[PDB]
Length: 141
Length: 141
Length: 146
Length: 146
Ligand code: HEM
Ligand code: HEM
Ligand code: HEM
Ligand code: HEM
Image: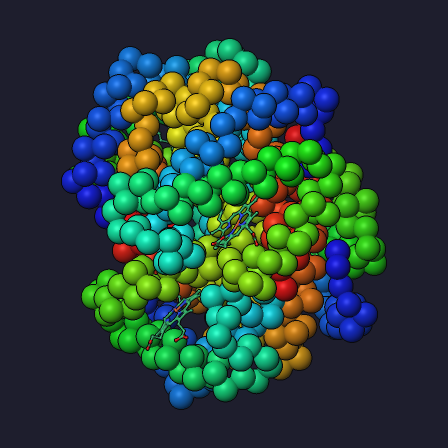
C-alpha cells in the first residue's frame, strides 16, 4: 500500500526536516492540544502550556519513533513493535486521535517547508502517517 | 488480525444465519439508510423506502460477498479482489461509511440471534467487518 | 435533539421495558470486551485483563447501571441534553479525563444491546430514533470539553 | 461557532491576505490528489487521471476558487453558519448527492493550505481558531441532509 514513490516522498520529506524533528513534533502536539482539546484527556499528568518540559520531552520521543518508521518503510510492523504493544496494552489511545496528530504533523511540515510540501508529497505523507497509526493500533483487539 | 477463535465465532454466526443472509443484509442496509441518512448520497438512483425491492436485491449481492468472505477468512484480499477494485475505482465510497453498515450488520445479527451474539462473538464479528471494510478500501490510494 | 412526536413515543415506550441493571451491566461489559482499550478507565475496579474477568467484575456491572440510569435521565429532557448533561460533561473532562470518543462507542453498543433484547420490536425506525438519541447524549457529554 | 474576540480578529486578519483563486485552486486540487475517491464528483471536469492533470485542470482550479469565495462569505456570519449555508446544504444533499464527510476532508486540506501559505504567522492559536471554523462550516453544510 505504500508505493515506492510514497516511500521516496516520505524519506525526501523527513530528510528536509533534518535536525528539526523533535521541535517540529513538539510543535505538532501543541497544535493538537490547542485545536483538538479532547486529545488533552490523555495527558492529565502533563503541563500542556507552551514550552513545558513534558511536551518537549514527548515531542522528542515521538519524533524518534517517526524517524525509525521513516527508516523501516518496508516493515513498519517490525520497527514499531514495542510501541505497538505499549499503545495497545497500556496507553490505549482511542484510534481517532492518531488522525488528529497526523493532521497536526502535516500542518507543521507544510508551514515549515512550504515549497517542498507538494500535493503529491502531501498525498504520500498522509498515507504514511495513516500507515503508522494502523500499525500502532494493530494489537488493540 | 482475526485469531482462530474470532474465525470460529464468525463461522458459527454465519452458519446460524444460513438462508437468512439476503434478508439479514437487506435489513442491515435499511437500518443504515434510515439511521444514517448520509449513506443514501451513494444510492440516489435507488428506491430507499421501507421494504424496498431494490434494497432487497442489493442485500442479496452484499450477503453473497459476506458469505464468500466467511468462506475465505485466511485470504480476504483474494476473495474480495473484484469488489475492492470496484469500490476503489468506481464507487469510491468514503471509508467512513463502511463502519455505518458494519454497525447495522451487528444490530441485525444481535436482533435475530441474541443467544449466539455474545460479547465475545460481538467482538469477533466487529473485527471481521472492519477487516472486510479495510479490504474493500485497500485500493483507494 | 430533533425528534418527531412518533419517535419520542417510540423512545419512551422501549425504555420503560429496559432493565437498567441488566442492560446497563451488559452495555458497559460489551464496551470493554469489544473495544478492550476502554478498560483503561476502570482498571481500579479489579482484574479486567480478560473478557471473562470484565463480565464478572461487580464494579463494572454496577457502573453500567449507573451510566444507563443517567442515560435514562437524558430521555426525560430530550429537548435540552446540553443542560441536563452539563455538570457530567465537566466532570468527565476535568476530573475523569475521559476521551469523549468513548461516548460514541458506548452509544453504538447500547443500540446493539437494545436490539439484542427486544428483537422484532427494535425496528429500523425504532433504531433511527435511538441513534439520534445516543448521538445527542454523546454530543452533550462532550460539549463542555476544553 | 464560538470564537473569542481575539480568535475572530485572527480569523478575519488572515483571510484578508488570502488569495481566493490561488488557495482555493490548491485546496480543491490537494483534496483530489490526497483523497482520490473525491474525484467521483468531478468526472465531467476533464482529465483527472494524474496528479499533474488535476493540478492543471482549469475546471478544478475554477471550482476551488468558487468554493473558497463561499467559505469566505461564511466567515462574515460566524455566529450563524447554519443559516448562511442552509441553501447550499440542501443543494449538496438533494442535487449533488455529496457525502458530507467530504466537507470535513476539505476543511483539513484548507487548514493545511493556509499553514503552507502563511508559514509561521499561522500559529497554533491561529490554527485552533481556524479548526473551529472549518468544523463549523462542515457542520452547517451537513445540517440539511436527510
Ligand atoms: C494523538 C495521538 C496519540 C496520543 C493521544 C498518544 C498518547 C500517548 C501517551 C499518553 C503516552 C505516554 C506519554 C508519557 O506519559 O510520557 C505516549 C507514549 C508514546 N507514544 Fe503515543 N500517542 C499518540 C500517537 C503516537 C504516534 C503517531 C506515535 C509514533 C511516533 C507515538 C509514539 C509514542 C512514543 C515513542 C511514546 C513514548 C514511549 C516510551 O516512553 O517508551 N504515539 N503516547
Ligand atoms: C462492507 C460491506 C460492503 C460490501 C460487502 C459491499 C459489496 C458490494 C457488492 C457485492 C456490490 C454489487 C456489485 C455488483 O454485482 O455490481 C456493491 C455495489 C455497491 N456498493 Fe458496496 N459493499 C459494502 C460497503 C458499501 C458501503 C458502506 C457503501 C455506501 C454506503 C457501498 C456502496 C455501494 C454502491 C453505491 C454500489 C452500486 C449499487 C448499484 O449497483 O446501483 N458499499 N457493493
Ligand atoms: C462511554 C463510555 C464512558 C466511559 C468510559 C466513562 C467513564 C467514567 C468513569 C471512569 C467514571 C468514574 C468511575 C469511578 O472512578 O468510580 C464515570 C462516572 C460517571 N459517568 Fe461515565 N463514562 C462513559 C459514558 C457515560 C455516559 C454515556 C453516561 C450517561 C450520561 C455517563 C454517566 C456517568 C455518571 C452518572 C457517573 C458518576 C459520576 C459521579 O456522580 O461521581 N457516563 N464515567
Ligand atoms: C469538500 C468537498 C466538496 C465537494 C465534493 C463539493 C461538490 C460540489 C459539486 C460537485 C458542485 C457542482 C459542480 C459544479 O459547480 O460544476 C458544487 C457546487 C458548489 N459548492 Fe461544493 N463541494 C464541496 C465542498 C464545498 C464547500 C466547503 C463549499 C463552501 C463553503 C462549497 C460550496 C459550493 C458552491 C458555492 C457551489 C456552486 C453552487 C451553484 O452555483 O449552484 N462546496 N459542490
